[PDB]
Image (cartoon, rainbow, N blue to C red):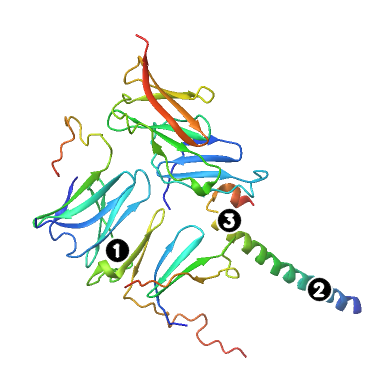
Amino acid sequence: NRIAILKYAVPFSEELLIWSDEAQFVLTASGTLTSKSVELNLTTQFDVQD
Amino acid sequence: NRIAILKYAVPFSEELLIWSDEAQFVLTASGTLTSKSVELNLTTQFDVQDRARPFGIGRNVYFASPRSSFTSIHRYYAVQDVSSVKNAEDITSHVPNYIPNGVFSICGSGTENFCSVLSHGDPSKIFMYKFLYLNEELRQQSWSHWDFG
Amino acid sequence: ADLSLQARSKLEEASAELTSQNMQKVQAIGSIRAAIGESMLEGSSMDRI
Amino acid sequence: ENVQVLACQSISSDMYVILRNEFNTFLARISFTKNAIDLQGEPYRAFMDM
Amino acid sequence: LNTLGDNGALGQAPYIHLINRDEHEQYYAVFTGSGIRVFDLSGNEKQVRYPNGSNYIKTANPRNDLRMVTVADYTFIVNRNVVAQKNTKSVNLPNYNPN
């Protein structure tokens, strides 16, 4: 619901963290990524800067 | 992402530990090994060296990390829950500068609760390390040496 | 001349079957390529499967 | 003074830092080993900064 | 360890990214404001040649505008300013009247 551009992404292992100015995301798939099971959740709301 | 050569592998039932310098691995399959499901995971990042002979008394593995002189022994506890691997902690923190340097063997007894490090820096001495593990809590660790003449 | 046309029909039935079997192939081979890549293991054995 | 630290980057056991003087640019490493001496000889692990 | 060069040999504000491929091969990919220099951790400078041109590195402030990832052997480099563009005049068939 808020047009947030994506600036930082840190891949760990089984989860990718997407960081946008005031909302943060986790990209986790389970098993293979595969597109069908790509998934994304809005975890935190803290502020990051450019 | 880092070309790591493989030096040490300590077989356990269920899991095999692969120890590159700067990267450590566990080879666990579940059921049969059966090529298909062989699996491998990057557990820990601690530093091992070429002459760091690892000898695993039980669940935990002791390996000597050579300094410029007076090596310091390190201990890594291979936990079945790969979630809690943490890192390899030093066991000669209280007694550094003690082992001479060139270590050619690490031997111990699980039943007798000790491991002996003998080094060619000072051939005569056998550096005893006696420990007493109680339900994963380190009750006592003692460093001493035996001089045979 | 009927059987000659009928031979062409069996060619088309075989041709349609090969495409249908080929659709499942690229899905199945493509899916395996996904897991071997993410398996971070590489080597000759994974090239074999 | 007048020294700019361009980049400090760390390998697992020691960190290699390259720093710029107003005349030169140098490469040097800071080693975090517990007791070991940095150079041969070196009676007591001297702290001479270069 | 060995001196890299003169004061101005590197950029005024360079982007420096350490490379760790092997226990034997370790480097520092420092980006001048225009151009690249690559030194080994021993201090020796390994010369860089720019086939296929450069003009991708040239940046007023390379610290902010460069994002790199060091894979096993070589590193991918993004200039944040440069906008990706589709290649016109490379069509599969120029006209190809279908009928």
Label 2: which residue? C13
Q: Nearer the viewer, residue D40 or B123?
A: B123
Q: Quadrant of the N terminus of chain D?
A: bottom left
- Is residue B42 at all visible to an observer of this figure? no
Label 1: which residue? E50
Image-based side of A5 in relation to E30, left or right: right
Mark linked to residue E17: none
Give the quadrant of residue B74.
top left
Distance CA(mark 2)–CA(mark 1): 56 Å
Mark linked to residue C36: 3
Distance CA(mark 1)–CA(mark 3): 34 Å
Secondary structure of the residue carrying tag 2 is helix
CB-based contact (under 8 Å), mark 1 and mark 3? no
Image-based side of C3 in relation to A39, left or right: right
The picture places residue B62, in percent across and down from the top left corner, at: 44, 32
Residue type marked 2: Glu
Q: Nearer the viewer, residue E87 or D26?
A: D26
Crowding at mark 3 (Cα within 10 Å: few <14, some 14-19, many 20+): some
Give the quadrant of residue E9.
bottom left
Q: Quick check: do tags 1 and 3 share a chain?
A: no
Q: Residue furthest top?
A: B149
CB-based contact (under 8 Å), mark 2 and mark 3? no
